[PDB]
Length: 130
Length: 131
Length: 120
Length: 119
Ligand SMILES: [Cl-]
Ligand SMILES: [Cl-]
Ligand SMILES: [Cl-]
Ligand SMILES: [Cl-]
Image (cartoon, rainbow over all chains, first blue to last red; front, side, top):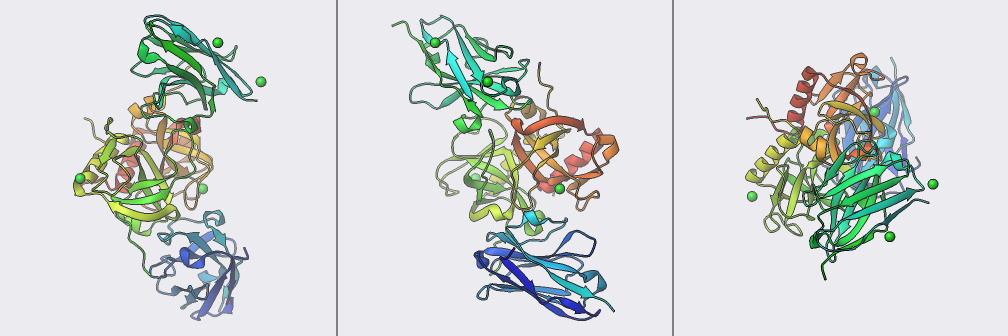
C-alpha cells in the first residue's frame, strides 16, 4: 500500500551493512507499532522486528537479534532497519507493516500474513551474495 | 420477508391454561433453534424455554419448568408453548425468537437481550388475573 | 516511549466488537488471564469479560468485583466462561489490577470453567 | 431430531469470523475445552483454535495432532493461546474428538497458557 513506502534496498556482500527506511503517510504514524517482515525468494512471510508506537520497546526474531536494529522517527513519519553482519539467508523483499494501539508491538513466533496488519508496505529488495 | 407471528395469548384466571403459537416464514425454520422469552411491565427480558432446530432437545427456566411445555412442528413451520398451572407472575408479553445452528438451543442463565437472537416475533400478551 | 507492561490480573478497556449471539461484546473492561511471558512477547493476550448487567456471582465460574476498589462504573462480575484471545491492538487503556485474593478466585473459576480440576 | 451432545475434547468446525490482527479467524476446526456441564446447558462453548500454518509445536502451549487419526486436511497444531468463547450458533459440524492422551496434553498446555500451574 502507498501508506508505507520502503527504500534503501539493493545488492550487498556478506558481512556488509544496509539501512532500510519506510515512509508513512495517510495514517497516524506515532500511534502505530511498526513491523519489518521479509519474504525470501520461495518462502513465506517471516517476521523480523517490531517497535512500539513510542519507540521505547523493540523485538527481534532470533535469527536477526543483535545484527539488526529497528528504530523510528515519529517527527519524520519514518521507520528504519539498520542491518549489520548481513548473511545470505537475509536475501528477501522487506516490508514494513503497522498495527494500531499503545500496547501493540511484540515478538512473533509464527508465520504472519498481510491481512493481520492494519497497513502493509510496498517492499524493497535486499540481496546478499559473495 | 422474515416474520415470526405469535398468537394464542389472552386473559385467563389463575390455574388456567393457554397454547401459544408462533408461525415462521421467509427463512428456513428447520435450521434454527427456537426460544420463548417473556417481558413483564417495567422488567427486563426473561428467557422461558428453548427447543433445538430438530425438536428433540428442550430447556426450561426454573420458574416455568413442569408447568410449560415447548414443542415444534417443522412441517407447519410453527413453534408452540403449552402453558398450564398459570399464575399471576406469568402475566407478560411472550416472544418467540430464533437462533441459527444445529447445536443452538440451551438453558439461559443471564439476562437476555434482543441482539442475542437472530429473529424476533412481535409478541403475544398473556394476562393471568381473577379480576 | 516504552511499553506499558501487561501483567496477568490487569484490567484493561478493550474493544470486543463485533460479537454474535450470547458472546460479550462492545467496549468494556477485561481482565488479563494469560501468563506473564505470553503477555510480554506475544501479539495476543487472553482476557475474561467483565459485565455490569449482573450483580451477584450466582454460578461458580463468576467472580464479583467491587466498584470502589477497582474503579468501575458499578459492581460488576468477571465472567470466566466469557474468554477470548485479543490482538493487543484491541487494548485501549489500563483501568486497574486485581488483588491477590481476587485473582485466586479467578484462578479457581478458570479451573471449573475449563474442566481442569483433577476430580479423582 | 435431537442434537448430539457437545463434549469437552470434541473437534468441531466453527465460524470464528470476523477477527482482527493475529487472532485466528475464518471457518476452521476448534477443540471444545469448556467443562461438560457448560457444554450441555450453556448458550456458549469455550474453544481452542487449530491451525495448519504450522505442523510442529512452537511453544509449550501448542499441541500437535496428526491429520490421519483426527481426519484433518494436514498435520496441524492446537493453539492453547488462541482460545475464545463462542455462541453455539457458530458450531457447524463435529469433525472428531481427541484421545485421552491428547486431551492430557491439551490440559497441560492450557495450564501454562492461563498461568494456572503450582509454585
Ligand atoms: Cl390471536
Ligand atoms: Cl417463505
Ligand atoms: Cl479483594
Ligand atoms: Cl491459519
